[PDB]
Length: 174
Length: 174
Image (cartoon, rainbow over all chains, first blue to last red; front, top):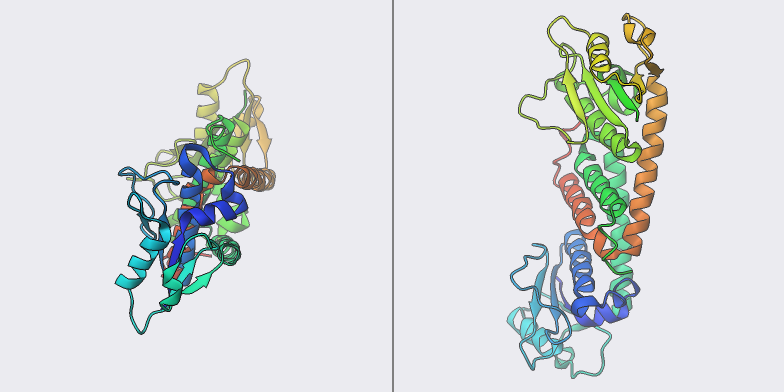
Protein backbone atom coordinates (compact mmCIF):
# COMPACT_ATOMS: atom_id res chain seq x y z
CA UNK A 1 1.76 -3.35 -0.75
CA UNK A 2 0.00 0.00 0.00
CA UNK A 3 1.27 3.49 -0.99
CA UNK A 4 -0.34 6.56 0.73
CA UNK A 5 -0.65 9.81 -1.31
CA UNK A 6 -1.61 12.69 0.99
CA UNK A 7 -3.43 15.94 0.06
CA UNK A 8 -1.31 18.07 2.41
CA UNK A 9 -3.37 21.30 2.34
CA UNK A 10 -6.60 19.35 2.94
CA UNK A 11 -5.14 17.68 6.11
CA UNK A 12 -3.95 21.09 7.35
CA UNK A 13 -7.48 22.58 7.05
CA UNK A 14 -9.23 19.53 8.59
CA UNK A 15 -6.99 18.59 11.58
CA UNK A 16 -7.58 20.66 14.78
CA UNK A 17 -3.86 20.72 15.75
CA UNK A 18 -2.98 22.00 12.23
CA UNK A 19 -5.79 24.37 11.02
CA UNK A 20 -4.67 27.25 13.34
CA UNK A 21 -0.92 27.13 12.42
CA UNK A 22 -1.60 29.55 9.48
CA UNK A 23 1.45 31.91 9.81
CA UNK A 24 3.81 32.30 6.78
CA UNK A 25 1.53 30.17 4.46
CA UNK A 26 0.90 27.34 7.04
CA UNK A 27 4.69 26.81 7.61
CA UNK A 28 4.21 25.31 11.10
CA UNK A 29 1.19 23.21 10.00
CA UNK A 30 3.26 21.81 7.06
CA UNK A 31 6.19 20.90 9.39
CA UNK A 32 3.90 19.18 11.98
CA UNK A 33 2.12 17.25 9.18
CA UNK A 34 5.47 16.00 7.71
CA UNK A 35 6.55 14.77 11.20
CA UNK A 36 3.16 12.99 11.69
CA UNK A 37 3.61 11.33 8.25
CA UNK A 38 7.21 10.27 9.24
CA UNK A 39 5.71 8.42 12.27
CA UNK A 40 2.97 6.86 10.00
CA UNK A 41 5.54 5.71 7.38
CA UNK A 42 7.88 4.21 10.05
CA UNK A 43 5.14 2.42 12.06
CA UNK A 44 3.21 0.95 9.07
CA UNK A 45 6.11 0.40 6.66
CA UNK A 46 3.87 1.94 3.95
CA UNK A 47 5.37 4.42 1.48
CA UNK A 48 4.02 7.97 2.15
CA UNK A 49 4.05 10.91 -0.31
CA UNK A 50 2.78 14.33 0.85
CA UNK A 51 1.54 16.66 -1.91
CA UNK A 52 1.25 20.36 -1.09
CA UNK A 53 -0.50 22.89 -3.31
CA UNK A 54 2.39 25.43 -3.89
CA UNK A 55 -0.09 28.39 -4.08
CA UNK A 56 -1.46 27.70 -0.50
CA UNK A 57 1.48 26.12 1.42
CA UNK A 58 4.93 27.70 2.01
CA UNK A 59 7.70 26.08 -0.06
CA UNK A 60 10.73 24.41 1.51
CA UNK A 61 13.40 26.54 -0.33
CA UNK A 62 16.37 24.08 -0.07
CA UNK A 63 15.40 23.23 3.62
CA UNK A 64 15.80 19.45 4.04
CA UNK A 65 12.75 17.49 5.31
CA UNK A 66 12.28 14.11 7.06
CA UNK A 67 13.99 11.28 5.09
CA UNK A 68 10.97 9.04 5.86
CA UNK A 69 8.60 11.33 3.89
CA UNK A 70 8.68 12.33 0.24
CA UNK A 71 7.29 15.91 0.05
CA UNK A 72 6.14 17.23 -3.38
CA UNK A 73 4.92 20.72 -4.25
CA UNK A 74 2.60 21.24 -7.26
CA UNK A 75 3.69 23.36 -10.31
CA UNK A 76 2.06 26.79 -10.85
CA UNK A 77 -1.57 26.19 -12.13
CA UNK A 78 -1.44 22.50 -11.07
CA UNK A 79 -3.74 21.27 -8.28
CA UNK A 80 -2.88 18.55 -5.71
CA UNK A 81 -5.34 16.09 -7.35
CA UNK A 82 -3.50 16.46 -10.72
CA UNK A 83 -0.08 15.79 -9.12
CA UNK A 84 -1.53 12.88 -7.07
CA UNK A 85 -2.90 11.35 -10.36
CA UNK A 86 0.58 11.70 -12.05
CA UNK A 87 2.25 10.04 -8.99
CA UNK A 88 -0.32 7.18 -8.90
CA UNK A 89 0.18 6.57 -12.68
CA UNK A 90 4.01 6.57 -12.32
CA UNK A 91 3.76 4.05 -9.41
CA UNK A 92 0.81 2.05 -10.93
CA UNK A 93 1.38 -1.70 -10.50
CA UNK A 94 -0.90 -4.82 -10.19
CA UNK A 95 0.65 -5.88 -6.78
CA UNK A 96 0.22 -2.36 -5.22
CA UNK A 97 -2.82 -0.51 -3.87
CA UNK A 98 -2.84 3.33 -4.06
CA UNK A 99 -4.58 5.16 -1.18
CA UNK A 100 -5.32 8.90 -1.36
CA UNK A 101 -5.87 10.89 1.85
CA UNK A 102 -8.39 13.70 1.06
CA UNK A 103 -11.88 14.89 2.11
CA UNK A 104 -12.01 17.46 -0.78
CA UNK A 105 -14.81 17.23 -3.38
CA UNK A 106 -14.22 20.61 -5.16
CA UNK A 107 -11.61 19.03 -7.50
CA UNK A 108 -12.12 16.37 -10.19
CA UNK A 109 -10.09 13.63 -8.35
CA UNK A 110 -9.97 11.64 -11.65
CA UNK A 111 -7.64 9.07 -9.94
CA UNK A 112 -10.63 7.68 -7.95
CA UNK A 113 -11.90 6.21 -11.26
CA UNK A 114 -8.46 4.59 -11.87
CA UNK A 115 -8.39 2.08 -8.96
CA UNK A 116 -7.16 4.42 -6.17
CA UNK A 117 -8.95 4.25 -2.80
CA UNK A 118 -10.12 7.33 -0.94
CA UNK A 119 -9.16 7.85 2.72
CA UNK A 120 -10.86 10.71 4.58
CA UNK A 121 -8.97 13.46 6.53
CA UNK A 122 -10.71 12.25 9.77
CA UNK A 123 -9.67 8.58 9.11
CA UNK A 124 -5.98 9.55 8.55
CA UNK A 125 -6.05 11.74 11.73
CA UNK A 126 -7.43 8.86 13.90
CA UNK A 127 -4.77 6.48 12.48
CA UNK A 128 -2.05 9.13 13.16
CA UNK A 129 -3.31 9.77 16.77
CA UNK A 130 -3.37 6.01 17.56
CA UNK A 131 0.15 5.42 16.00
CA UNK A 132 1.54 8.44 18.01
CA UNK A 133 0.19 7.00 21.32
CA UNK A 134 1.44 3.48 20.47
CA UNK A 135 5.01 4.67 19.61
CA UNK A 136 5.08 6.73 22.87
CA UNK A 137 3.92 3.71 24.97
CA UNK A 138 6.50 1.41 23.36
CA UNK A 139 9.31 3.99 23.93
CA UNK A 140 8.24 4.51 27.62
CA UNK A 141 8.27 0.71 28.15
CA UNK A 142 11.74 0.06 26.62
CA UNK A 143 13.36 3.19 28.20
CA UNK A 144 12.04 2.06 31.66
CA UNK A 145 13.59 -1.39 31.05
CA UNK A 146 16.88 -0.06 29.57
CA UNK A 147 17.60 3.31 31.37
CA UNK A 148 20.77 3.97 29.25
CA UNK A 149 18.56 3.91 26.10
CA UNK A 150 16.57 6.95 27.44
CA UNK A 151 19.60 9.38 27.62
CA UNK A 152 19.34 10.90 24.05
CA UNK A 153 15.55 11.29 24.55
CA UNK A 154 15.86 12.85 28.08
CA UNK A 155 18.47 15.29 26.66
CA UNK A 156 15.88 16.35 23.98
CA UNK A 157 13.11 16.63 26.66
CA UNK A 158 15.49 18.84 28.75
CA UNK A 159 16.39 21.03 25.71
CA UNK A 160 12.61 21.58 25.05
CA UNK A 161 12.04 22.51 28.78
CA UNK A 162 14.91 25.06 28.65
CA UNK A 163 13.74 26.47 25.24
CA UNK A 164 10.26 27.04 26.77
CA UNK A 165 11.63 28.61 30.02
CA UNK A 166 13.81 31.18 28.17
CA UNK A 167 10.83 32.08 25.91
CA UNK A 168 12.20 30.48 22.69
CA UNK A 169 8.79 28.84 21.92
CA UNK A 170 6.75 32.08 22.45
CA UNK A 171 7.05 32.94 18.68
CA UNK A 172 5.31 29.59 17.74
CA UNK A 173 1.49 29.34 17.21
CA UNK A 174 -1.18 27.49 19.27
CA UNK B 1 22.99 29.93 46.00
CA UNK B 2 23.33 26.14 46.70
CA UNK B 3 25.93 23.67 45.47
CA UNK B 4 25.29 19.94 45.37
CA UNK B 5 28.37 17.65 45.60
CA UNK B 6 27.41 14.08 44.68
CA UNK B 7 29.10 10.82 45.76
CA UNK B 8 28.59 9.20 42.34
CA UNK B 9 29.50 5.58 43.24
CA UNK B 10 27.23 5.71 46.32
CA UNK B 11 24.19 6.82 44.19
CA UNK B 12 24.92 4.03 41.68
CA UNK B 13 24.87 1.34 44.41
CA UNK B 14 21.75 2.75 46.16
CA UNK B 15 19.36 3.62 43.25
CA UNK B 16 17.36 0.62 41.85
CA UNK B 17 17.56 1.74 38.18
CA UNK B 18 21.38 2.21 38.56
CA UNK B 19 22.69 -0.66 40.81
CA UNK B 20 22.26 -3.34 38.08
CA UNK B 21 24.03 -1.36 35.26
CA UNK B 22 27.41 -2.83 36.42
CA UNK B 23 29.01 -3.68 33.01
CA UNK B 24 32.42 -2.09 32.13
CA UNK B 25 32.85 -0.54 35.68
CA UNK B 26 29.22 0.83 35.90
CA UNK B 27 29.54 2.72 32.53
CA UNK B 28 25.76 2.76 31.90
CA UNK B 29 24.97 3.61 35.57
CA UNK B 30 27.47 6.55 35.40
CA UNK B 31 25.87 7.86 32.14
CA UNK B 32 22.27 7.60 33.51
CA UNK B 33 23.37 9.35 36.76
CA UNK B 34 25.01 12.25 34.82
CA UNK B 35 21.78 12.74 32.78
CA UNK B 36 19.67 12.71 36.01
CA UNK B 37 22.05 15.32 37.51
CA UNK B 38 21.73 17.51 34.31
CA UNK B 39 17.92 17.55 34.86
CA UNK B 40 18.46 18.38 38.61
CA UNK B 41 20.92 21.23 37.82
CA UNK B 42 18.62 22.72 35.11
CA UNK B 43 15.37 22.51 37.14
CA UNK B 44 16.77 23.81 40.49
CA UNK B 45 19.39 26.23 39.14
CA UNK B 46 21.78 24.71 41.74
CA UNK B 47 25.36 23.96 40.76
CA UNK B 48 25.94 20.15 40.62
CA UNK B 49 29.31 18.38 40.82
CA UNK B 50 29.46 14.58 40.50
CA UNK B 51 32.50 12.89 42.10
CA UNK B 52 33.34 9.37 40.99
CA UNK B 53 35.85 7.15 42.74
CA UNK B 54 38.28 6.37 39.80
CA UNK B 55 38.96 2.79 41.07
CA UNK B 56 35.24 1.80 41.02
CA UNK B 57 33.71 3.81 38.13
CA UNK B 58 34.80 3.75 34.45
CA UNK B 59 36.65 6.91 33.36
CA UNK B 60 35.24 9.29 30.73
CA UNK B 61 38.39 9.02 28.47
CA UNK B 62 37.10 10.46 25.12
CA UNK B 63 33.47 11.13 26.31
CA UNK B 64 32.68 14.82 26.71
CA UNK B 65 29.78 14.69 29.23
CA UNK B 66 26.71 16.95 29.68
CA UNK B 67 27.74 20.66 29.88
CA UNK B 68 25.12 20.96 32.70
CA UNK B 69 27.19 18.68 35.00
CA UNK B 70 30.76 18.92 36.19
CA UNK B 71 32.11 15.34 36.52
CA UNK B 72 35.29 14.78 38.61
CA UNK B 73 37.23 11.55 39.07
CA UNK B 74 39.39 11.06 42.22
CA UNK B 75 43.23 10.67 42.05
CA UNK B 76 45.05 7.31 42.76
CA UNK B 77 44.67 6.81 46.60
CA UNK B 78 42.04 9.52 47.03
CA UNK B 79 38.49 8.72 48.13
CA UNK B 80 35.33 10.60 47.03
CA UNK B 81 34.92 12.17 50.51
CA UNK B 82 38.47 13.69 50.26
CA UNK B 83 37.77 15.18 46.78
CA UNK B 84 34.33 16.42 47.95
CA UNK B 85 36.06 18.19 50.93
CA UNK B 86 38.64 19.85 48.55
CA UNK B 87 35.77 21.01 46.24
CA UNK B 88 33.72 22.39 49.17
CA UNK B 89 36.80 24.28 50.49
CA UNK B 90 37.61 25.69 46.99
CA UNK B 91 33.96 26.89 46.60
CA UNK B 92 33.53 27.94 50.28
CA UNK B 93 31.81 31.39 50.33
CA UNK B 94 29.57 33.27 52.90
CA UNK B 95 26.43 33.37 50.60
CA UNK B 96 26.70 29.61 49.64
CA UNK B 97 25.35 26.39 51.28
CA UNK B 98 27.20 23.14 50.39
CA UNK B 99 25.08 19.96 50.19
CA UNK B 100 26.68 16.50 49.90
CA UNK B 101 24.68 13.58 48.48
CA UNK B 102 25.87 10.35 50.22
CA UNK B 103 24.51 7.53 52.45
CA UNK B 104 28.07 6.16 53.09
CA UNK B 105 29.38 5.94 56.68
CA UNK B 106 32.59 3.90 56.01
CA UNK B 107 34.59 7.07 55.21
CA UNK B 108 35.52 9.97 57.49
CA UNK B 109 33.33 12.59 55.70
CA UNK B 110 35.32 15.36 57.51
CA UNK B 111 33.37 18.00 55.46
CA UNK B 112 30.23 17.33 57.60
CA UNK B 113 32.07 19.09 60.48
CA UNK B 114 32.80 22.10 58.19
CA UNK B 115 29.22 23.38 57.61
CA UNK B 116 28.23 21.04 54.73
CA UNK B 117 24.78 19.41 54.89
CA UNK B 118 24.25 15.71 54.30
CA UNK B 119 21.66 14.52 51.77
CA UNK B 120 20.94 10.78 51.65
CA UNK B 121 20.93 8.65 48.48
CA UNK B 122 17.15 8.02 49.00
CA UNK B 123 16.45 11.79 49.37
CA UNK B 124 18.35 12.68 46.17
CA UNK B 125 16.54 9.85 44.29
CA UNK B 126 13.07 11.12 45.53
CA UNK B 127 14.00 14.69 44.38
CA UNK B 128 15.29 13.37 40.99
CA UNK B 129 12.10 11.27 40.42
CA UNK B 130 9.82 14.31 41.18
CA UNK B 131 11.91 16.68 38.93
CA UNK B 132 11.89 14.09 36.06
CA UNK B 133 8.04 13.81 36.19
CA UNK B 134 7.62 17.60 36.44
CA UNK B 135 9.91 18.34 33.43
CA UNK B 136 8.08 15.65 31.37
CA UNK B 137 4.63 17.11 32.28
CA UNK B 138 5.71 20.70 31.41
CA UNK B 139 7.19 19.51 28.07
CA UNK B 140 3.96 17.54 27.24
CA UNK B 141 1.88 20.65 28.12
CA UNK B 142 3.88 23.16 26.00
CA UNK B 143 4.29 20.74 23.01
CA UNK B 144 0.47 20.15 23.01
CA UNK B 145 -0.05 23.95 22.98
CA UNK B 146 2.70 24.67 20.38
CA UNK B 147 2.77 21.59 18.02
CA UNK B 148 5.79 22.95 16.01
CA UNK B 149 7.84 22.88 19.26
CA UNK B 150 7.37 19.05 19.48
CA UNK B 151 9.07 18.17 16.10
CA UNK B 152 12.72 17.73 17.40
CA UNK B 153 11.38 15.69 20.35
CA UNK B 154 9.04 13.49 18.19
CA UNK B 155 12.02 12.81 15.89
CA UNK B 156 14.03 11.61 18.95
CA UNK B 157 11.01 9.48 20.17
CA UNK B 158 10.80 7.95 16.63
CA UNK B 159 14.61 7.29 16.53
CA UNK B 160 14.34 5.44 19.91
CA UNK B 161 11.37 3.33 18.56
CA UNK B 162 13.37 2.38 15.44
CA UNK B 163 16.57 1.65 17.50
CA UNK B 164 14.50 -0.74 19.69
CA UNK B 165 12.76 -2.44 16.68
CA UNK B 166 16.07 -3.20 14.87
CA UNK B 167 17.55 -4.59 18.16
CA UNK B 168 20.03 -1.71 18.77
CA UNK B 169 19.04 -1.52 22.49
CA UNK B 170 19.47 -5.32 23.11
CA UNK B 171 23.18 -4.78 24.14
CA UNK B 172 22.07 -2.36 26.97
CA UNK B 173 21.42 -3.59 30.57
CA UNK B 174 18.13 -3.82 32.56
